[PDB]
Amino acid sequence: MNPDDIVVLVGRKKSGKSYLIKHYFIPVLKAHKISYIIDDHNSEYSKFGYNATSLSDIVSKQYVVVYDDFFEKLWQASKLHSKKYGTTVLIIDEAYYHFKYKQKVTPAIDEALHANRHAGLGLILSTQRVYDLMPIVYKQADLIIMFYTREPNELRWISKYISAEAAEKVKTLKQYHFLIYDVNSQTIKIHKPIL
Ligand SMILES: [Cl-]
Ligand SMILES: [Mg+2]
């Protein structure tokens, strides 16, 4: 993950999405001195950054958790954060609320999908089913990560918007194993569980 990449995480609850964030993305971000802002809508990430009580905290604290009209506020605050700390990763553990399939696209959502680099903000979006998010999220993504599924509608979406090969290989992943799809290079890795 480049610091201004868009990364999508896809898998049913308990498949290991938050674990990957906590144990794979966050530590590597930290090691490069890459800032992040975690937008938690379900706390679970309490120990990974300053727990914010205001928009000012989002801007000023280097590693920050936010407990979530609001997306535009969050987005504006993140842009100001990035100007202070350099490229920042905005991590959203419930992309289902702002990026939902068949929803409109505000200027801020559009910016987040098409103008990341310019705003100095990477994105990690997390979702339980592939068909929860707008197909344009899959087109705009740089890396798509998928855990096991054989739900036939999900296979169809993966095949149509991502890769027919990924749709095949997704069906055989063991627990905590995950497929990585590089949208740009069009390659596929099958990764073992994180330690
Ligand atoms: Cl709008
Ligand atoms: Mg989770």
Image (cartoon, grey):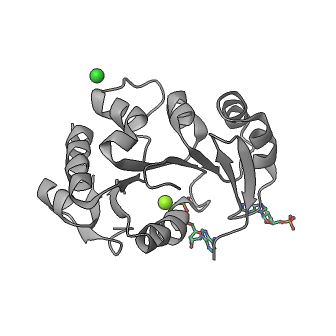
The residue nearer to you, when weighing 2 against 144, is 2
The residue nearer to you, when weighing 94 against 56, is 56
Q: Quadrant of residue 39?
A: bottom left
The residue nearer to you, when weighing 186 against 57, is 186
- Picture coordinates of residue 34 (x, y %)? 38, 64
Position of 52 with respect to 120 (left or right) is: left
Q: Quadrant of residue 66?
A: bottom left
The residue sitting at 56% across, 55% down in the picture is: 13
Position of 48 with respect to 194 (left or right) is: left
- Picture coordinates of residue 27 (x, y %)? 47, 72
Q: Answer above or below: position of 17 versus 129.
A: below
The residue sitting at 41% across, 49% down in the picture is: 122
* Residue 87 in view of the camera: yes
| Quadrant including the C terminus | bottom right
Q: Answer above or below: position of 41 versus 97.
A: below
The residue nearer to you, when weighing 163 against 40, is 163
* Residue 127 in view of the camera: no
- Picture coordinates of residue 102 (x, y %)? 46, 24
The residue sitting at 36% across, 72% down in the picture is: 48
The residue sitting at 26% across, 67% down in the picture is: 62
Please state the total of marks drawn on the protein image: 0
Position of 186 with respect to 83 (left or right) is: right
